[PDB]
Amino acid sequence: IRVGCHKLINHHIFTNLILVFIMLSSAALAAEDPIRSHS
Image 1 (cartoon, one colour):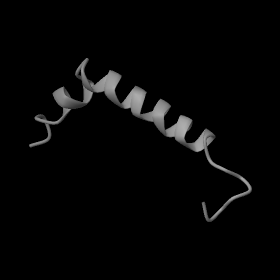
Image 2 (tube, rainbow, N blue to C red; image 1 turned 60 degrees about the horizontal axis):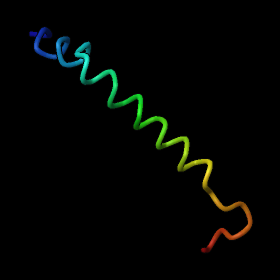
Image 3 (tube, rainbow, N blue to C red; image 1 turned 180 degrees about the vertical axis):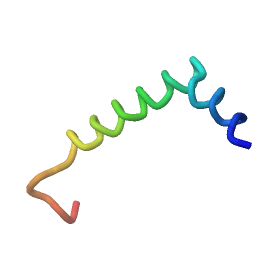
């Protein structure tokens, strides 16, 4: 069956946790040091 995953996908809780993981990922990307590669 392929019904037990749709509720988890479209749940209100699961649409506001990944939206902050992506913000943290972008922030971590923005904090990279361009000069010091081995730092």
